[PDB]
Length: 234
Image (tube, rainbow, N blue to C red; front, top):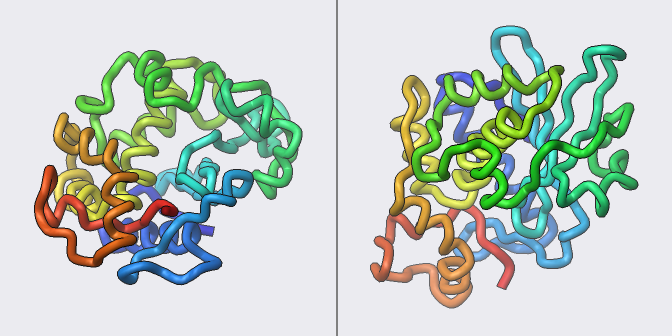
């Protein structure tokens, strides 16, 4: 299972991302030597372990395999010390019944999380935009601590989720974003900004072209910005 001890070691971060990318694309050939997701994997998930170096506490993220979309996470209940599965409010009805098939080690199904999985609701609950949310190792460690084993609030959960999406999912999709995290988010914090946010929104459109050519050429975005680490099915 892909795992990353949230720390300032960029080599481990990059290896973690490659492991994650491969999991999304297992089963069929790569394109331009880039893994590709499977459209039929909408009912399959890829688990990711995030571990704090300080106390070794662990939170397991669950991503829908067809589109690398975060649907929830697993941590430990403070009263029973059991592993509990937590799903976003808009994914709970569809996945709660099969919590054990998604979170392999879950011991109990916890109540639905105080927020939804969409970018719109996540930002509303967190009270901050994708563009100015503070990203980086320290930022993620702090958000993690406000969530693991505690009472969940919409804000704490939403913030933790957004930082994780940027540093794990978006970085997996875009080599350019992985590079930004390596250079600006290992020992410090940084904000994604408007251009990177628009780049992220165009994952599907860029992916489409990669299925037709391995050398795209500059357009709305540069060739480097378009260098994908994971392709969407076509």
